[PDB]
Image (spheres, helix red, strand yellow):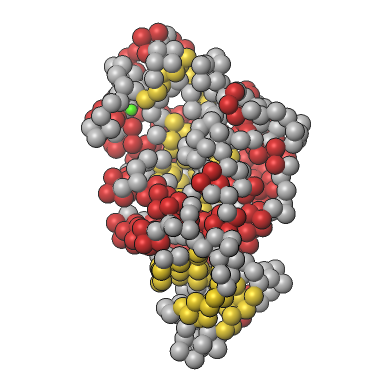
Amino acid sequence: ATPADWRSQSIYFLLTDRFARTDGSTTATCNTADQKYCGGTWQGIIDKLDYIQGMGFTAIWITPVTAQLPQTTAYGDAYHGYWQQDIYSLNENYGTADDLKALSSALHERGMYLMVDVVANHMGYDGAGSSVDYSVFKPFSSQDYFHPFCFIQNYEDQTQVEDCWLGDNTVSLPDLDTTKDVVKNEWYDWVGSLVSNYSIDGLRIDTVKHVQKDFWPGYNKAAGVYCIGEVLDGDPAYTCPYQNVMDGVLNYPIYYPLLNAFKSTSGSMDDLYNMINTVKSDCPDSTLLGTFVENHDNPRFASYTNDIALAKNVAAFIILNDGIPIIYAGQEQHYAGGNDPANREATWLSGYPTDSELYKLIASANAIRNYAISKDTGFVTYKNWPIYKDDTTIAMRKGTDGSQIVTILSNKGASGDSYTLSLSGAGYTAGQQLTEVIGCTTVTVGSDGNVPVPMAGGLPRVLYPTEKLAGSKICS
Ligand SMILES: *[C@@H]1O[C@H](CO)[C@@H](O)[C@H](O)[C@H]1NC(C)=O
Ligand SMILES: [Ca+2]
């Protein structure tokens, strides 16, 4: 599927090892500190697609599918998929080639997309760099395919970042020489044939900044589908230029201020408001970035605060921001694990309740986005407009004039006081009825064109014209 096809999608990101077992158990042990395979599979995902689709997601992002190092290392198993050795075999822990094809077709039968995580930068090996037997890597079965052994020490030296190895003396990540034509041609043939064999709709590419830029346009072209890169830098001047070589990047620039804004009642709405406007003007296309606050590489949002109103607000933001919403399996059940491995909790241990507070919030937010998009082909290309901020508030507008979603978010938290925020700049006309589609209340635009927004319980407010909700299942 093209970058234009992907603009309207909403992604549920999951760890294949941690989301669903074939036996559908909600009680099988998964102690994250063990760092071992807990038994999740492609078949388990198929069996829980109703759970995912019930929150209004249109797509899933699964962890890499290639065969891994076999060892249980001092850091555990390759349960995460980022330690590949044989790219022409699948990780049999998750199932067979027929199971991955059955997952692609099950998503396609529901009108959903499959996005698959891939690594081009490195292989994985149990042991120090000097111990590596290059013959285990398929097809890169020789030292000749790899950069000379060194670790990245100076992350300010882009040459060392690209040419030296990640990992450490316990688990080595042998760094492919991605400047060699033979490595380019191998990766390019592989990625086109992966997408083609499994009917994959898009790729998330791990570890983009560690591969030199001239590798990426050939890779994105070979895949023949939307590619969203992991470029791990909060500076849009470093990260946004990668959109010149790849369709999308994960919105790490928005991540840091978005987390800060909602993780405490002290959070800076200024830093978030300012970064939205920097990304909107200085990134090649803000509408092809991936918005998130939670993944398997950072502490979960609930690890910073268990305030459910703050979690509702940050989820509403992720879904209503420019670009593609990405929610990480467990976020919807308020999971609170810290850094790796604590943030790889098994989704099944929740029991997959469809009545949890954040399952319901995400369902409501995805419902108005999915609905608004079905009635407004301009929603996804209208750049999100922050129209208001104060110490505890940010409001933003997105969508074609007369159909705009107007979102008011708060970091007051669940103890927040009850008041009326007189909001200017929403662009609706006096007497217009709006539905607040999270709480299903109506608000009427005033004589002066200001919206009297009811604030209470630190709750997020999402406004849309009541007349435009004709015939939708929202707030029935
Ligand atoms: C796709 O299938 C063909 C077998 O026809 C094979 O030549 C190729 O290696 C496969 N690609 C992947 C990535 O499995
Ligand atoms: Ca590299």
Most foreground residue, 338 or 29? 338
Tally the numbered discs.
0
Image quadrant assignment for residue 224: top left
Q: Is residue 30 above or below residue 69?
A: below
Q: Residue at x 70, y 32 (%)?
A: 21
Residue 110 visible: no
Most foreground residue, 429 or 264? 264
Direction from residue 60 to residue 221 in the image, left or right? left
Direction from residue 130 to residue 85 in the image, left or right? right
Q: Residue at x 59, y 66 (%)?
A: 457
Q: Extreme bottom residue here?
A: 447
Image quadrant assignment for residue 132: top left
Assign the C terminus to one quadrant of the image.
Answer: bottom right
Q: Residue at x 47, y 73 (%)?
A: 400
What x and y, as percent, mark residue 321? Answer: 46, 60
Image quadrant assignment for residue 312: bottom right
What x and y, as percent, mark residue 447? Answer: 49, 91
Residue 27 visible: yes
Q: Is residue 191 above or below residue 335?
A: above
What x and y, as percent, mark residue 57? Answer: 61, 52
Most foreground residue, 126 or 338? 338
What x and y, as percent, mark residue 422? Answer: 48, 80
Q: Residue at x 53, y 28 (%)?
A: 81
